Image (cartoon, coloured by chain):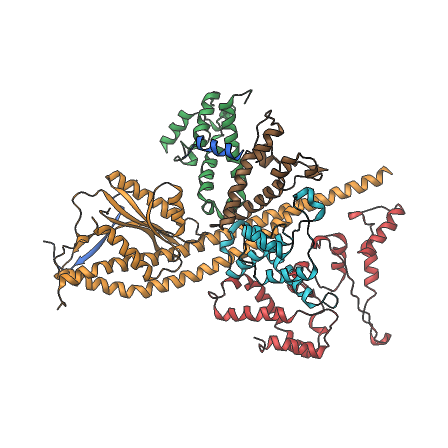
Chain colours: A brown, B blue, C red, D cyan, E green, F orange
Amino acid sequence: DGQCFLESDLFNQGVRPAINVGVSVSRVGGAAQIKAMKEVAGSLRLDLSQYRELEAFAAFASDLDAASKAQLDRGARLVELLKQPQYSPLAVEEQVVAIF
Amino acid sequence: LVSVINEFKKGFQASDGALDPEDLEKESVKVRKPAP
Amino acid sequence: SKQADAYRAISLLLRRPPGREAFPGDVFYLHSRLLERCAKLSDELGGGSMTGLPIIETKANDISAFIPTNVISITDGQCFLESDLFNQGVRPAINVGVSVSRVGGAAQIKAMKEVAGSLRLDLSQYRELEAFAAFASDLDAASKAQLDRGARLVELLKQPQYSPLAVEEQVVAIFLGTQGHLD
Amino acid sequence: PAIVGDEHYRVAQEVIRILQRYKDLQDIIAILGIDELSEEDKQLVNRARRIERFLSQNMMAAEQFTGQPGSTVPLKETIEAFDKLTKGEFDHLPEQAFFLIGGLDDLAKKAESL
Amino acid sequence: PAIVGDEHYRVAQEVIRILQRYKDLQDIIAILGIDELSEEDKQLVNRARRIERFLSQNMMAAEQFTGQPGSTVPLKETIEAFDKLTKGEFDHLPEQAFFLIGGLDDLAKKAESL
Amino acid sequence: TLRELRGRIRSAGSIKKITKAQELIATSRIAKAQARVEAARPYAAEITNMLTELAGASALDHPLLVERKQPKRAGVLVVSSDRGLCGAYNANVLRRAEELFSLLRDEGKDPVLYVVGRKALGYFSFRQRTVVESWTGFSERPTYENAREIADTLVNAFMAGLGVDELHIVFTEFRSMLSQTAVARRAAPMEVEYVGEYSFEPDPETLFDALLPRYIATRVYAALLEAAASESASRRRAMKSATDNADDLIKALTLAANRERQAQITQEISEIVGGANAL
């Protein structure tokens, strides 16, 4: 029902766990989350994949539109937020606030 | 939660952060009279 | 291509030995003994003729697959149709930069030779110049004209389906472009 | 164009031409950057990056994927929206405004949000 | 970090991140050279090339071929050197200075002769 | 797998077309730039002759001809490209700029920086030093209208002594199509070179005090035309390099794609024939 494609060239660049957010999906989706998480995170996969498409595109653009620069900085914030060390589980009550 | 985040943000602390004079060249103005 | 796939199905069910791309050994001979029956007969046999247009379908535009390679080696001329040119508006999608015919001028009427003679050269020069379209101000005028001719010839070669033109109308169509009246 | 009418066929063929040209230019843009391209090509790229996202749609079965409800866009509205896009009548909207949006009424409201 | 300690692990992760970003930029580096890269990347590649060359060592075995003697460096000196390299305390030295060194005092001794 | 190599071959084969196109473009533009330089030269040669005949009669006491008693601060102009793909051009300029700054700070002076061209503006914004003023959007075709504003600004900053005790320019001299380098030189104060041996309206002193700023403008203009011609020549060289590098990449990828094609076919055959021999 879904893929958590772990990619070594994301793992090496600090993104741990190394989920390739383009290919990774869950097809049961937000039917398998508590209401708070569906409110807070209800599009986060699409927003990160759009950020990875934009980060690839804008890599060598000398200047960027105001909305583009906002999305590119928001994505770097979300990617830094999703990093997590080994054996540091978060209770769902802590995860909701972290994504909030 | 928003109120707690904004109370906390004021109290956070971020980690905020050989040429040779003989090879240098001179512009000149010429004068067709001998040096004093 | 579905001819060759049917003969592969039959041959494998009969436990004949498979070769490259699972085809039986004789698949070249299967296509050849079909195609080489197309010919023009001499006058002693009544001067009749048969012209073959074999179609084949190529996976992902490769031409190094077994059946393509055989039929390209058997046939006299090869009109490559490319889906990229199809999408870029060139319909029919004839890749005039790679399609060839070994018969050449001997199949054309004199009025077509008198016009089409430079056409392949003009389109080759246009395909070479194509990158300079972005910088056409800085290009020398003597080749800026070649670029503008080439772009008009590429428009002149488009054609709607089910509307074939008789020879006397297409010669006039190519005359417009080649003689520069269209510019 | 004998079946669907010449309006539909023209709009479809213009959109495909634009997306094909954009797929040719991606390999350049990924190395040399969009700033290198001609003004006409750079304009086409800005139209294509919008067209791609306006081909996305919030489907009614994707309620559990996107949380937003689904929408149905009429054939005439589809033809008119893409016709306007290809001529650049929406080039001044921000690139994210088109994504998942559905029809022109929703497009306007989401552009006015941003 | 539990087995080797934080001071080892943090350095190792920083080195791997630098070498990974260099191994990603390799595709452009091969066509356009260093000069096309933005400053945040060109700063990285300059020290990546140094970190990469500095991972070489004159091994005791190779003495029978090169004639240079072998070198042993303790773990602590290795951690200190790569921490300094990643932060940039050696960026001003030429890449050629870094081949087949061993430890930091041998680096200095080599860099003085150039 | 083969599909990535087929894509990468097509990509590289587009990049090879686009770099070869720009190499030919740059080979045209260096001729345009040399034509502009040779069209500008016959003004500068006559302003120089007139300036020397005025200096022959003048007092020679204009501020630009007299050094300060103890200099603390020196203005520098760096000129750079507005577009990428120039290769070493901006790096050579900015390496010479830092080498000049380490001369000045070794003499005791601090540089105050003026920048031409968006590349050097991006460099001096990444390294933390402030720029006093900058100009962009003409390094591909400089016109005298820009050199007027730059020369005005630099001369006003000099004559103020915030103020500066000297003026320097960093640029590149076009020695020949195959050879060029960055150069740094002092524009003010100016040296006076005596050499071996007219009416003036209203006076030689007044004319000389009006002319010197316009001489400084024509010299910065001649430097901007040299910068643009050398930039386009460096672009030509760097684009010929990029084309050769793409051609060698298409070769290597093709040689990989062929080894992959052959291996794929041989594997497919080994699998079929093993299937047959099992029966």
Which residue is farthest right?
C14
Query: In the image, is F154 to the left or to the right of E36?
Result: left
**Front residue of this view, candidates C112 and F73:** F73
Which residue lies most toward the left here? B36
User: Left or right of A25: which side holds E70?
Assistant: left
State whether residue F12 appears in this view.
no
Q: Is residue E43 above or below residue C83?
A: above
In this rendering, the answer to whether D70 lies above or below F201 is above
Q: Quadrant of the C terminus of chain E?
A: top left
Instruction: Tell me: A16 left or right of A61.
Output: right
User: Residue sitting at 51 percent across and 57 percent down?
Assistant: D37
Q: How many marks?
A: 0
Q: Residue E4 location in percent, x, y? A: 53, 21
Query: Can you give x and y, in whole percent of width and height, for residue F161 in the image?
Result: 20, 48
Residue A40 screen position, x and y as percent: 60, 38
On screen, residue C109 above or below D66: below
* Residue A36, image x, y percentages: 63, 35
Outermost residue toward the front in this view: B3
Quick check: can you spot residue C40? yes
Residue at 84%, 60% (x, y): give it. Answer: C33
Quadrant showing the N terminus of chain E: top right
